[PDB]
Length: 129
Figure 1 (spheres, rainbow, N blue to C red):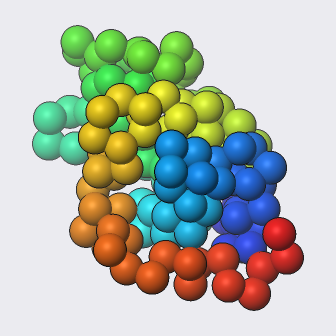
Figure 2 (figure 1 turned 135 degrees about the vertical axis):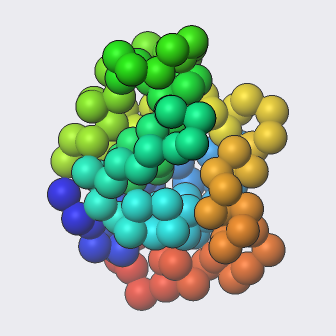
């Protein structure tokens, strides 16, 4: 499913991501834009052999099981294909563990590089939330 900017903002909100660990909604929406272009079906393989899945591009080295990443840890306890669904619930629950992990949203490279220190509020402007 390719979400609309405001549709995604609204679902993320409803899912408890707004201000989750001090990161406002605009942060989450910006990171989703840059990680997957709002497409829940986005996948990207990494040099290490791991793969990023879904709207939030969650890595199979640590967070989910895809059956082909040796030494994966499966911290979110889910198969990686669950992260590709039209329903963002598992992506969200998993992102919440990730962000609680220590480095915050810095875990997301596009967030760090394209979102961080920018006017992220722009991302939810005009939305009915």
